[PDB]
């Protein structure tokens, strides 16, 4: 009941998704071959939410992995933990989008969008009671941002009364992976603010910074990087997968987290984060967990909250604890740090508690904050896009495959409108 | 599933291609005969696997004089190439652009296109053509301008990358180099997606200083150039943490349609003995590849401003130090970017350490970098070449050979003004603008 | 005889997707709503008739084609018209008929350039020509 | 009880019949040598419908294979599973019809039809209570088409009060196997429309697409194509061959499917069709069975039902299931796809259920649809024939052996009348 | 169980038959002495089996000059042929159609007919005749016309296929070729079901280019033609997934009574060295056999429109890719059919891979294609021959010889008018018309 459909687009989505189904399988005790090997019967009480029952007690994930180039599917299929995905869902093209909007939303996207949409429609009919969709993609690439938006537009047309989340990977302020980042990002957000209920923005250096100082890792590869994102994205869902003292679900978070339709860009966070060596000198208890997750150092988006004010905040604990300890400290955090919370929203903290701890830990938590400091991220991106567009640089490879000048103009005006209203509420009395 | 074919034109292309295809067989473990003793396929992008275990390359060797092709036929790689692919004429163009484009080339152009279409239709997911041609020669310039016009008509929008050989500033093998180079650039300007520039004079110094070799024959230079070519297409044949394709190169380096002349660079380039005393970290080969003396074209990037770059690592490379090293490079005051390009870096990481050909000068390295900088400093190269062409053409020297072979004096003037249009186009956008 | 033109990479000359559909609709006075609907080739055959009087037997083609086999016959007539006028652009008929945006947009992009090169400004009513 | 006489014509009929008898022997547990080796007695309960008992407990099929050229007979006799047919039934000529209606209907037809009629009469008098006739052939070849028409006419004359099915391989739109297809196709279809009862049109290109796309086969061959066709035929006959919860017969299918005498051209389909690799990731159940059945891509006739309306539909399940599920999902399909169903025929779905699953499968299903998309096939054939006959091509070689232009004119008129009536009944309110 | 007999007339017919019977003996595993060490019957269709294990062919070698027949008699295939079958005259026709049809040829026709009748009555399921003859040769032409008349009189309606040798447009061995060819075409236009047409110049060019032999004597041409004939007859001789017959060929290829002159093509024709570097797929062998330069008659089908095509694949052939390749070929730009033939392909598949003669030029292949195309481009050849005949006859050259050997100029005039009518009919039927 209330199962969700997982869609992975681009190379980042496939690499994040490959580590995501590693954690989910471990939580439910599913062998890589696809058969249940767990012990506690609480795991199989709600297995239909993510996995799908098949013949001979085999379980197949409800995932749809799609990328425009065949490089990514080669690794996941041939590599380990690729014997359990359903081979029908492995949809791929032949030529990459080439870091282009047009070659990922109009020219190459159209060929593949009709094939994936039929796989999506098949899963829903098999589904008993749909809950929503989950999308992991990037805002800098061509297929992850171009076509990933195309699925959002088409799916939102067929299932208007559903809630879907995007675990995007927002670009960087310091070093840009691709030269034409602003053209792809600005055009993407102009489509995301319309057909998405809630979006979790994630950076890469704030993940490098966390994995450098807090985790004590000098050489964090992409395997140790995506492993941090997976826990955050699996922490949100775990409320409905397992019983808890004070339950929550995907729709419950959206009601509390989103005061206004255009203000649905979040900043995740995880705790506890400790190195292997220094875990024996800390007593795992609720006091440090709330303290640890509320500092700007341990946040997964490179945006310091001290420059803004939290509109509303969620905190999805896990493990087992005492409800008094949890509620005692949220009030303490609010009163002491009262200068960073908006005034026209009282008691702006939402708390939920589950009952199943993560693997190898007594208790943990996930912090989701709809802060105002996100305004600075959009201000910077619109700054880079503005300078490039006046000189009309790199643009003769976006007009050549379908768009025009008028499309960019409407994308920047919408982007500038969102920043103005994201700030005029911070200063509103 | 992904196929790209390579066309080698002239002696420079064939001699480079002879060294390059020696490297691919080593990388994929293909014996010279064809049999064999990341890998599951890999070789399918270059080697079309035939009925038996034999693999035959997707190459088209075309030349007008039969002197050098015959060397390849009798060489150690005799059983590899498809005998029909090696196309030969009867007499060379003799450093004459008109002969290799109007009179002699026209009689063999139809046969070459026949073999191209046969190989293209055999493949299914064709991406683009790799062209290895020189600039000073007759068949390497006049004939290669004919192939671009013919190829572009047949296949509308496909990648077409040129690995040219720019004439050197002081070193000069031929004497009519300004006449040939000026004419070629004006004709192939509209039919090239991205042309990589490599100069013979600059490679001599790199081999002399860094590699410390005082006997750098043409065999040694071609091995060093071939490593650049392999790193460009190393992402198609091998997996990696962050892949790039042939199209991604084209979209990230060309801000304007005329400005598509980047210059390559390789790192590290060290000898066998100097290798032990160097720790060879990621944070320094990025620094090494940016030094003004390591650039493969005889021009200092300090005199101009960078427009876009493209790094390509391979081996035991972790993305955290890659992004840390680039951040330090950006804040260095020697490297200066243009105002209208706030983002100026594209990265790509591969998991396949570069291999070494036996008897080669380069040592075994677990890390490598290939840099494709599209910079304004190349505008100096155009100005110098235009100076030579204007000097000799004023008194109409050597023209009587070109005119009498199916050309007009009027055609020279059109190619002269076109290069003048490109020269100030290159400067007027690299310079700042008001507001 | 007819003049030819190539198209590889041009700036400030390629038109938007919306404008290309308007030009096709305006020239023939019809209601194509998607560019990918140009898989039929009925509009393509009419273009050759406008560019060069005759050279195409417009009676052979039919504008009510709705099947995969029906789409091909319309293009075979266009193949002969290209040969007769001596043009040398190979139509990838195996790829247009599938009705996808990629291949259908590139061919009209080339055809727009061919249209301008061989247009003498003559005008007529395609309605009587079509019926 | 209720025995069926099988007739095979031409190379296509012979090969399809060879595969069909392989499948039937596998179903009934009959050794290639002709002796019973299986286990369950439910197979022996009704063995006289197809086979025929003989001394020393042998079983011989009631099949009459006959074709003008001998090569097919030599192949079927020398090959395996040729030791069980009765040699008396092996009838053949000396020279093929040469893809000619005249040589297939008047020249060699006389001798071949005389001998075949004698054999048919002997077999029928041997039979106890005849149920009907089965004829598998092609409408493009000479011998199969012409001599099958002659056999149908003579048998219809001899036994007016009986039913006969014709499994005809209709020509393909893209590529034609023989240059003069339309003349033979038009004449044969005119004769079939005149004097046949029901006809399942089967195409080759649609089978090719089904095998390449769904079954995921790199090199689909005639063995596989004939395997699919034989599976369909066995699924049709299993209802009266085996006991079931809700039995059905050939007469029941005919009366439920045929509303008017000139409308008896069906399109078959079989489910489930899965590749070797992907069978483990699917749950064999009635919902997915019906959803797989009711999509155009899994249709064996190269006609898209989306272009027309289903006049009537029959569905023969196999194996063990639940009638509640069966009729619930039939109702769901009818409600969801109502716009594709004719308005003046309510409840236009017939359902039958057997009890013995096919070999190596828990359950399966055969769907037979009488639709209005065959209108397009008849229209295309009529157009091709009209062009060729207007230009008067190849026609001297049908006049040179007996016929005249009057026959062609009347056949064309009949085809046009039939297609016009089909369309005009499609467009009724 | 099905028997067809072959008549070889003239030196060209005898040599082609020698090559063809060598190929058949190799294919069916029959030793030259007649003994032997799909297949079981097969050889029954050609080789009549006598009391002992010896097999004798159903061939009738007829000639007027005894030299070539004596050569065959003393050749290595001496014990095979029935000695009574080899019929020889005393003096040749000397390139004189009148001598070979009226004066000399009337003195041996009765014996030839008697042998044909005995061989036919020996068999019980007679299918047809295969006549191997040239066109320029006087005895070939005259005796071919006489045999056509006599056989048509004797047996009413049977398949009578011919394998002619059309005179080359430029290469010429005789001087009265136009007279002989025009006369023979007018005489045997009515008594032939289907005539396959082959030219020597095109086979020369094919052997020079594709097979790359610079010394192509008549043996190689004979081997190629024999391969085509065996590919045609393989459907009768062997089982397959989709069989065809002589009546099928005839019906599917002749649309009009006068238009029964198709042309043949074979694929693949590649040497041994080039075989390893080729994959030999069904699609590409179809493309090669349909390529314009591979046609075995010196005429370009691009100049005309196709009317009917018959493809015959033999070997490891899959009908799915066969049908895919045929659809692609139909979609291709070069192939253009006539408006009144919406269906234009007849396909046959055989399960027997082609065999290779020992010492032959061709290489072993697992897939073979024979293409028989009836088209319009033969009209240009007819017009050229008519022009040559008119130019020669305008001033009555060699007409003294022809008239002296029992003919009249009325016959020449009638042949000319008949050829003109045939050309007019061919052009009118090929050209499109409104309504
Ligand atoms: N978190 C995370 N991000 C990644 C990882 N790999 C790449 N990225 C980011 O994702 C972007 C990759 O581009 P994609 O959206 O995947 O584009 P693509 O799949 O290569 O297809 P094209 O856009 O056509 O090249 C890069 O800019 C990186 O910043 C990863 O392993 N983990
Ligand atoms: N890098 C490199 N360049 C070469 C090599 N061989 C020749 N060249 C270049 O080629 C130029 C000589 O003209 P080519 O392009 O070879 O002309 P060609 O191929 O001989 O044909 P013709 O012009 O007709 O003589 C010289 O200026 C060199 O710069 C080589 O081995 N390596
Ligand atoms: N389903 C299926 N169809 C086939 C197969 N083989 C051939 N066909 C079709 O059946 C037709 C065969 O012609 P036939 O009716 O058998 O005629 P024939 O046996 O060759 O005898 P003639 O008509 O005298 O030539 C072809 O047009 C094919 O389209 C097969 O193996 N399976
Ligand atoms: N393809 C092929 N053609 C041949 C061969 N031998 C002879 N010819 C053809 O035969 C023609 C010569 O006339 P023939 O048919 O041989 O006449 P003949 O057998 O010498 O008898 P006469 O006509 O009396 O001289 C030449 O034009 C050749 O084209 C051969 O071995 N192969
Ligand atoms: Mg990618
Ligand atoms: Mg040279
Ligand atoms: Mg037959
Ligand atoms: Mg002679």
Image: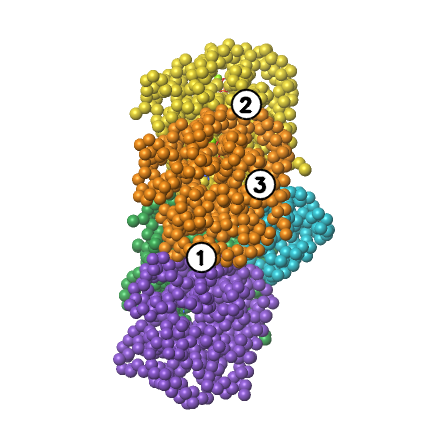
Chain colours: A purple, B green, C cyan, D orange, E yellow
Q: Chain of mark 1?
A: D
Q: Which residue is mark 3?
A: D261
Tell me the number on the disc at residue D325: 1
Most extreme residue toward the bottom, as rendered? Answer: A336
Sort mark 2 into few (<14), some (14-19) or many (20+) by Cα contacts within 10 Å: some
Does any portion of residue B120 appear in the rendered image? no
User: Residue drawn at (42%, 24%), measured in percent from left and top?
Assistant: E1
Residue C16 shown left or right of residue A171 in the figure: right
Distance, label 1 to label 3, CA atoms, is 34 Å
Residue nearer the viewer, B339 or A40:
A40
For residue B293, above or below residue C1: below
Chain ID at mark 2 = E
- Label 2, label 3: how many angstroms apart (C-alpha)? 47 Å
Number of residues whose C-alpha sits closer than 10 Å to that of mark 3, classed few (under 14), some (14–19) or many (20 or more): few
Residue at the spot of label 2: E192
- Residue at 56 percent of width and 70 percent of height: A411
Mark identifier at residue A200: none
Report the Cα–Cα distance between label 1 and label 2: 68 Å
Query: Does residue D353 appear in this view?
Result: yes
Q: Residue E318: x, y in percent? A: 43, 40
Are circles 1 and 3 on residues that touch, CB within 8 Å? no
């Amino acid at each position: 009941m209330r199962e969700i459909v997982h869609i992975q687009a681009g190379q980042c989505g496939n690499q994040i998704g490959a580590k995501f189904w590693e954690v989910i399988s471990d939580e439910h005790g599913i062998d890589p071959s696809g058969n249940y090997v767990g012990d506690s019967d609480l795991q199989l009480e709600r297995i239909s939410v993510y996995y799908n029952e098949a013949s001979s007690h085999k379980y197949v994930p409800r995932a749809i992995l799609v990328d425009l180039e065949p490089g990514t599917m080669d690794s996941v299929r041939s590599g380990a933990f690729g014997h359990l995905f359903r081979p029908d869902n492995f949809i791929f093209g032949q030529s990459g989008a080439g870091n282009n909007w047009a070659k990922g939303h109009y020219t190459e996207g159209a060929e593949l969008v009709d094939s994936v949409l039929d796989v999506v429609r098949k899963e829903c009919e098999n589904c008993d009671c749909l809950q929503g969709f989950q999308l992991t993609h990037s805002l800098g690439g061509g297929t992850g941002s171009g076509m990933g938006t195309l699925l959002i537009s088409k799916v939102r047309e067929e299932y208007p009364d559903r809630i879907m989340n995007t675990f995007s990977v927002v670009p960087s302020p310091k070093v840009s992976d691709t030269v034409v980042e602003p053209y792809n990002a600005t055009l993407s957000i102009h489509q995301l603010v319309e057909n998405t209920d809630e979006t979790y923005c994630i950076d890469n250096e704030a993940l490098y910074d966390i994995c450098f100082r807090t985790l004590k890792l000098a050489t964090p590869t992409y395997g140790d990087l995506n492993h941090l994102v997976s826990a955050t994205m699996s922490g949100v869902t775990t409320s409905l997968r397992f019983p808890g003292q004070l339950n929550a679900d995907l729709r419950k978070l959206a009601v509390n987290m989103v005061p206004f339709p255009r203000l649905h860009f979040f900043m995740p966070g995880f705790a506890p984060l400790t190195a292997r060596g220094s875990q024996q000198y800390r007593a795992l208890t609720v006091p440090e967990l709330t303290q640890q997750m509320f500092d700007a150092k341990n946040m997964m988006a490179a945006c310091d909250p001290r420059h803004g004010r939290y509109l509303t905040v969620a905190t999805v604990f896990r493990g087992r604890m005492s409800m008094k300890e949890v509620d005692e400290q949220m009030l303490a955090i609010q009163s002491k740090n009262s200068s960073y919370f908006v005034e026209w929203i009282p008691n702006n903290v939402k708390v939920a508690v589950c009952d199943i701890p993560p693997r190898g830990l007594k208790m943990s938590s996930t912090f989701i904050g709809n802060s105002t400091a996100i305004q600075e991220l959009f201000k910077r991106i619109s700054e880079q896009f503005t300078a490039m567009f006046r000189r009309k640089a790199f643009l003769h490879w976006y007009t050549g495959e379908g768009m025009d000048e008028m499309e960019f103009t409407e994308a920047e005006s919408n982007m500038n409108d969102l920043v103005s209203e994201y700030q005029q509420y911070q200063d509103a009395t | 599933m992904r196929e790209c074919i390579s066309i080698h034109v002239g002696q420079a292309g064939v001699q480079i291609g002879n060294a390059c295809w020696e490297l691919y067989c080593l990388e994929h473990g293909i014996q010279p005969d064809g049999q064999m003793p990341h890998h599951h396929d890999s070789f399918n992008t270059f080697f079309s696997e035939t009925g038996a275990g034999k693999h035959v390359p997707r190459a088209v060797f075309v030349d007008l004089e039969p002197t050098v092709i015959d060397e390849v036929r009798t060489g150690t790689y005799r059983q590899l190439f498809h005998p029909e692919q090696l196309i030969t004429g009867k007499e060379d163009a003799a450093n004459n652009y008109a002969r290799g484009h109007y009179t002699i080339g026209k009689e063999i152009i139809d046969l070459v296109l026949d073999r191209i279409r046969k190989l293209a239709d055999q493949c299914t997911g064709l991406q683009g053509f790799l062209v290895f041609h020189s600039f000073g020669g007759g068949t390497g310039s006049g004939f290669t301008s004919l192939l671009m016009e013919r190829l572009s008509v047949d296949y509308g929008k496909k990648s077409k990358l040129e690995f040219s050989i720019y004439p050197a500033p002081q070193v000069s093998t031929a004497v009519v180099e300004p006449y040939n180079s000026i004419l070629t650039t004006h004709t192939t300007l509209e039919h090239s997606d991205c042309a990589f520039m490599v100069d013979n004079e600059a490679i001599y110094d790199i081999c002399r200083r860094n590699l410390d070799i005082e006997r750098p024959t043409y065999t040694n230079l071609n091995r060093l150039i071939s490593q650049i070519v392999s790193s460009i297409t190393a992402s198609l044949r091998f997996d990696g943490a962050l892949n790039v394709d042939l199209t991604q190169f084209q979209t990230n380096l060309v801000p304007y349609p005329r400005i598509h002349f980047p210059l390559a660079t390789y790192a590290p380039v060290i000898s066998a003995e100097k290798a032990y005393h160097e720790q060879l970290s990621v944070a320094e080969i990025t620094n090494a590849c940016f030094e003004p003396a390591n650039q493969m074209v005889k021009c200092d990037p300090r005199h101009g401003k960078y427009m876009a770059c493209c790094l390509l690592y391979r081996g035991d490379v972790v993305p955290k130090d890659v992004n840390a090293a680039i951040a330090t490079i950006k804040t260095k005051r020697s490297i200066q970017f243009v105002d209208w390009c706030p983002t100026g870096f594209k990265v790509g990481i591969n998991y396949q350490p570069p291999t070494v050909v036996p008897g080669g000068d380069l040592a075994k390295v677990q890390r490598a970098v290939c840099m494709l900088s599209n910079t304004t400093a190349i505008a100096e190269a155009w100005a110098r070449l235009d100076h030579k062409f204007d000097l000799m053409y004023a008194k109409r020297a050597f023209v009587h050979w070109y005119v009498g072979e199916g050309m007009e004096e009027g055609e020279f003037s059109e190619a002269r003004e076109d290069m003048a249009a490109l020269e100030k186009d290159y400067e007027e956008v690299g310079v700042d603008s008001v507001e | 005889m007819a003049v030819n033109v190539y198209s590889t990479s041009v700036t400030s000359e390629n038109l938007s997707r919306h404008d290309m559909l308007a030009w096709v609709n305006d020239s023939l006075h019809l209601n194509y709503t998607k560019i990918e609907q140009l898989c039929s080739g009925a509009a393509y055959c009419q273009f050759m008739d406008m560019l060069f009087p005759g050279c195409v037997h417009l009676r052979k083609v039919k504008f009510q084609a709705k099947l995969e086999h029906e789409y091909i016959h319309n293009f075979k007539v266009l193949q002969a018209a290209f040969k007769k006028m001596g043009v040398d652009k190979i139509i990838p008929v195996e790829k247009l008929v599938k009705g996808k945006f990629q291949d259908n947009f590139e061919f009209i992009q080339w055809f727009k350039k061919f249209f301008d090169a061989n247009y003498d400004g003559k005008d007529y009513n395609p309605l009587l020509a079509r019926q």
